[PDB]
Image (cartoon, coloured by chain):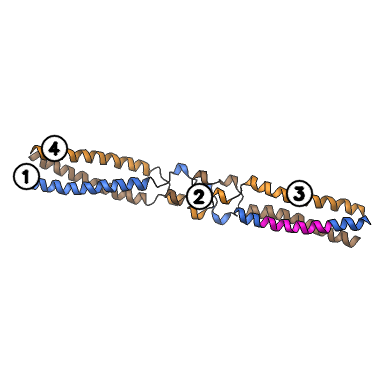
Chain colours: A brown, B blue, C orange
Amino acid sequence: MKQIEMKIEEILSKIYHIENEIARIKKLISQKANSQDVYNKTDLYPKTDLYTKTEMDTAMKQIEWKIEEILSKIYHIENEI
Amino acid sequence: GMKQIEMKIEEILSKIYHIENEIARIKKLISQKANSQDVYNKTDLYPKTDLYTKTEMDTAMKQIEWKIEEILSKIYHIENEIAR
Amino acid sequence: MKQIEMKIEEILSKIYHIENEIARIKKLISQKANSQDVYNKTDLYPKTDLYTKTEMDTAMKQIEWKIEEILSKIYHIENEI
């Protein structure tokens, strides 16, 4: 009988400690990202494989610059005719 | 005090039942979290704000092809003018 | 009495297993991504909504064609004058 009563208390202690761990785990869990709210590495391209807005604005301007270049000749050439 | 031991046993069981439920829930939730191994960090990626989509690019480009067409038609005409 | 001692042992068994699960959970938790260290799906575009560098370099080369067409004419036409 004295042993059972002692074991009861030991179990209760373990229960208290488990409940404390559970609370801590829940706090940490809530700081983790849900896979639902993120894309995997397979759903995405890295920085290295992509142009940003500016890199695109640059590439596009490269085309517009040559268009301007040509515009400046055309109207000189028509006026030369 | 057998009835009394039995009473503490019941109290324990109830706590145990609940802990078991929590554990099952936590494991479900854990399995919906993303492994840092399977994701790029913020430093390995650009945000929405720093990128153009495909359609925004396809849009910008066809606008560019419209001006090119325009300029082609001035050139054609200048070639034909000279010609005579 | 033998029944109470037998239930105690059943409880201890449950406790053993819960403790094992708790340790495991903590291990898995530590392999998860902090939401602080990632962008969500709303802060990003997927592979499907973006052109890579080569896809862009490809799309641009059709435009550079036409530019080369015109520039090459202009310069022999200026001589022709």
Residue depth check, mark 4 versus mark 2: number of the one nearer the observer: 4
The residue lying furthest to the bottom in this view is A79
Region in magenta: B60-75
Query: Disc 1 designates what residue?
Result: B2
Residue at 50% of width from left, 49% of height from top?
A: B42
Query: Disc 4 designates what residue?
Result: C6
Q: Residues within 10 Å of mark 1 (few under 14, many from 20)?
A: few
Query: Disc 3 designates what residue?
Result: C65
* Cα distance between the residues tagged 1 and 4: 14 Å
* Cα distance between the residues tagged 3 and 4: 86 Å
Q: Quadrant of the N terminus of chain A?
A: top left
User: At label 3, which amino acid type do we have?
Assistant: Trp
Query: Disc 2 designates what residue?
Result: B42
User: At label 4, which amino acid type do we have?
Assistant: Met
User: At label 1, which amino acid type do we have?
Assistant: Met
Secondary structure of the residue carrying tag 2 is: helix
